Amino acid sequence: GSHSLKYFHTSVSRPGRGEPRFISVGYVDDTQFVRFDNDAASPRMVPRAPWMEQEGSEYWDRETRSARDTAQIFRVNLRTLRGYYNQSEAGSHTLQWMHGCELGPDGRFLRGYEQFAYDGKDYLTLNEDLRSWTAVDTAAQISEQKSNDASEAEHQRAYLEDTCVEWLHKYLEKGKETLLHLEPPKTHVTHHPISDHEATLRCWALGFYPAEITLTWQQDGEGHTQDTELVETRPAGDGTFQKWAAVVVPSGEEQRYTCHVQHEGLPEPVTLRWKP
Amino acid sequence: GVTQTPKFQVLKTGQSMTLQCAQDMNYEYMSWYRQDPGMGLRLIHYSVSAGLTDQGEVPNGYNVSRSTTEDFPLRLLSAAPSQTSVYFCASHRNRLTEAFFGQGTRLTVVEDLKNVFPPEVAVFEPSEAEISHTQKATLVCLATGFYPDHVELSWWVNGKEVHSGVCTDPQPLKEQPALNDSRYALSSRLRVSATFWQDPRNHFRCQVQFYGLSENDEWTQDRAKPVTQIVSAEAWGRAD
Amino acid sequence: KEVEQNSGPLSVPEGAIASLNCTYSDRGSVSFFWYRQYSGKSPELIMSIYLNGLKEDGRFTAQLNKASQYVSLLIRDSQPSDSATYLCAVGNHNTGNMLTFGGGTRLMVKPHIQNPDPAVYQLRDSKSSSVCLFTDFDSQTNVSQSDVYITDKCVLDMRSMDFKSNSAVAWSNKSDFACANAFN
Amino acid sequence: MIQRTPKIQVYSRHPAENGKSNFLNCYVSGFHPSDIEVDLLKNGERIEKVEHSDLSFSKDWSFYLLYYTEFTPTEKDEYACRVNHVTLSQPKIVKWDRDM
Amino acid sequence: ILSPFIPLL
């Protein structure tokens, strides 16, 4: 089914403390796999998944160049946008760029995406047709026009539809064990007395991948108007993800309560109950 | 968009020379290609942005520098005959997108400046045979004994430049095909009706712009100094 | 040689479709270009293609097939203006050295000589002393090659008669100056 | 020019067992701009040799990072995360609860 | 891999 190859680019201006910071990270699905950062003597693209640790110098030399090139263009763009907005050299500014291509279950291009953001708001967006843009303002309109005159959308569509997809395949293969051989949640329920008369049941879901997951509490196998705390899905550090969902319930009614866990790595949804 | 200079240039083996290139598009990337006759462009050197350079396929003999965004001069260190070639500068927005080239520099390097000559031009007059057989008259032009191959031949009719009816040779002919340093010939045809030929108040001129030495070159031989110049020839129209 | 073109030259009849091909070795190539260069002048960009497929502008069509690593150009309704060298350029992302050029293919658009009247002439120097001139032959005649100086053939266009002759000059210094059978 | 204040979570990689080696995570997320200062604390003392993820961002453009260190939970020891940002008047400190 | 195509804004 749907896989994706995404890069996320960050350029931050550092007035008279060097040129701007540029960081680039590449994900397949929920798995970071490469990285570039211009804080070092040699800034080089580098692996950040064990399964890239065996890619040869042709890969790294090229992607190094590629990142460098983008960094340098992003310096230019930060200057340019300072201009369009008449801001001083003294201020620090952030330009961000996210792009990706997705596969369908057929193994083929499904959709592509590309967006720019100045100082944390949308600036310029590539439209779903990958043939045109959407500016948010006058400044962006100058950028729209420049891109139009340059057939940028064509060039990006070529990357997104073709090259992006070619390489997503290569990576999915190389990282099969991580990307395709999923990790179901290790799943359990803890009990935490609040007061004399009521407890928190908390349903854990640990070490799962990918990050998409659904935790649900049921009273007598049905919804409940009951306090339902749900924490943001969080990285364990090891490539997997964690999440819990708690409800507070009257002590001695913990058996009315069941946790429902849906995740792609399970063969089937699991239900769960506090075991004394 | 891209101003490259100069258009023509002769050089003595061992001389040094700097071709100029400038671009108003304010793009990061700039390049120097050379192109030998019948072949593709080959990349000499390029510059990813101000303050950077990289080598291309055939860097040897050449130096580049990128101080400004706008300019990217190419420097010949010590000229050799092998560096006789046409040089194109280009500007580019991204590394792998559209190259926008300049007008080009055609540059011949020669052992000794004694070997440069201007062209000897001669208008030829229509065959009488062809005047009756067709009622159409071909004026021929022939520019002889020039070197280097740096010429631009025009026809002017009553001191006005014509294009219709015209056909210059594409390349010139080596007077001596053996010698590497042979001089050149170049033919051209202006054809017009036998009626426009025989009106005697009509003037046909074959102009040939030549590019050789500058004023500040130094000449030490009996000939007149092969500077840049035109060389013309004419006939008038004839009642018959 | 990374970018292969055939030098030719290729002939196409005026009005006919011309077709020009290019192959390239590196699967890393991500951008593709057709440049037209008139003798003497600079390369001038005819068409640019990046996505696999067909792209059309005016009389021109380009087709890219990265699977088989060829790019091609088609010129509909060939005009004498289209006579030129055509340059294939790829952008190789694996090596990054700007655009890599093929050797070029020269295209000669030959016009249909209406009424072929192959005649040799002779023309007196407009100052005392003569040159030979093969003229009015047809576009399928190819002119043949010491001290016997023969040019290549070249086509003029009197517009006020919709007339086009081929014309190929020759001369010598010799007194022994045949001319009448100069073009054998 | 948007500014967004960091969300913080503090947790072990594996569920804590006193004496058994583990990892301590601080996950900051939801913040803009990028610049941010995170320390991991044992009993108020800053832990040296803490590492972190490369800087990435979400669909809303907000950034996220994971700071982490090897650690060996004990019954009595306390751990926490201290975070300072531009959106913060003074450091925020979040204490590690091992059941959270 | 990274895009070989980078917009100039």
Image: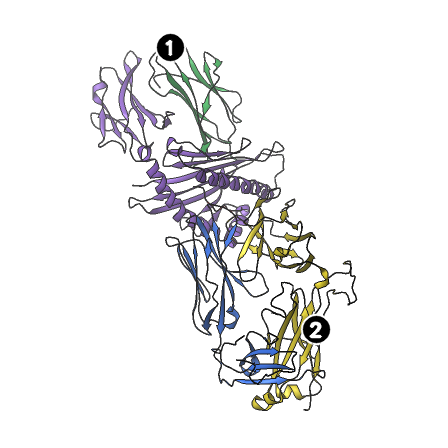
Chain colours: A purple, B yellow, C blue, D green, E red
Residue C52, given in percent of the width and then of the height, sits at 39, 54
User: Residue at point 34% right, 25% down?
Assistant: A242
Which residue corresponds to mark 2?
B120
Residue C40 appears left or right of A56: right
Q: Who is closer to the viewer here, B231 or B68?
A: B231
Which residue corresponds to mark 1?
D74
Chain of the residue under label 2: B
Chain of the residue under label 1: D
Q: Who is closer to the viewer here, C105 or A253?
A: C105
Amino acid marked by disc 2:
Glu
User: Residue at point 37% right, 10% down?
Assistant: D74
Residue C135, given in percent of the width and then of the height, sits at 55, 82
Q: Quadrant of the N terminus of chain A?
A: top left
Do badges 1 and 2 share one subunit? no
Asked whether residue C1 appears in the rendered view, the answer is: yes
Q: Relative to residue A233, is residue C151 depicted above or below?
A: below
User: Residue at point 48% right, 39% down?
Assistant: A61
Residue C40, given in percent of the width and then of the height, sits at 59, 65
Total marks shown come to 2
Q: Secondary structure at mark 2?
A: strand
